Length: 410
Image (cartoon, rainbow, N blue to C red; front, side, top):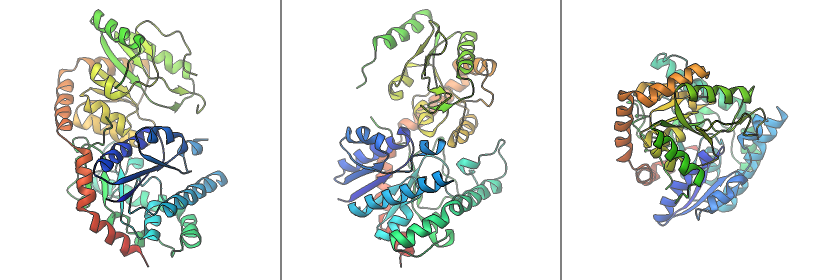
C-alpha cells in the first residue's frame, strides 16, 4: 500500500485520466494525491482524491521573463509539494518537467504517463513535430531526438540551477538523465496507438484511462428527439477552448456547413478572440449550443463527432464508435487527425470552411465503411482495460522503476 503522487499540468482533459487511475489505485488500497493547478481542486476532491496546487499552468503562457518566472513557479511549488508529502511512487505527465529531477532527489521510483508520442520510435514522430505528410521512419525517430534536445536546452540552465540550489543535486543533461529508460505508460488505446516493434519493454500502451449519472437538460432531450423525429442525422461539433481571428465568421461557417449537410448539430462552442462570449449570431433551430455535457453520455447518442482531436476527446469518440472529423489546432491534435485517417474511422480537416466541413459531415454521417471501422474500433476499445493494465504495469515495473531512479542518484 503505497503513497502515490499523480502530477500533471494543463487542462481538465489531462487531469481526468489520473482521477480515473487514482480511483483504481485507491480501490487497490493505495493512497493518491493528484498534484495540479488550483482550478481542478474541486474536480479532484469531488472524486474523493487528494489535491496539491502547483504553478506552470499552460494557459498562463498563451497570455521571456514571464516564461522564465512561469517555469520557476512550477519548479518551486512541485518541489515544495513532493518534498513535504514524501510520496513512495511518483507518476508524471512528462509535459510538467519536474518529476524526473524530483524523483532523483527523493530517491523514489518514478513513472511517466502520457497520451501522445513522447518516446523515441521510428513508427511515430514526436507529437509536437508531426509532419504534414507521413515522412520516413528515420524522420520520426529524429523528431524525438530533436524535441528531447530542444525541450531540454530551453529549460536546462534553469532546471540545473533549481537542481543544484533547491534540490541539492548535481547538474545533469539528457545523456545522464537517460529519460528513455523511465517506464512509460501511454494512456491510449493500442487500436489508435499500436505499440511499435522498437518500443522498450518498459514502454507500455495501456489502453485509455476512462472515468465512469448525468441528468440531461430538457432542452437537450427534446433537441435530440427532434433530430430523431425528423429522421435527420445528429452530430456533435466542439473544438474546446481555442482563440480565433473572427469568431462570428467561424460560427457562420459552422451554421452554413450544418445547413448544407442537413444535420442537427449539438454545438460545444468555446472559441472567441480572447482566452476566456458564446452566442454571436442567432443559432438556428437545428443547432443546439450547450455547454459541457459529458461525452461518455453524448457520443453514444449521436451519429458523428467533429472535434479538435485531442487524445481524450479522440478516445471518447472512438470509444463510442463515432465516425470522427478532426480539425487540429495545437499539439497532439495533429497526431490524432493523422491517426484517425490512417485507421479509416474519420476525416482530418486542414481547411475549416463551410465546404470542407459540409463534405466531412456528409461523408462521416453516411459512409458505411467508416461506420463499420468505427464499430470494429469500438469493439477493440470495449475489451481493453486501461486502468487494470496500467496498475498491472505499475506493479510489474516497480522494482525497475526504482533502479532507473537510483541509476540517476549520487
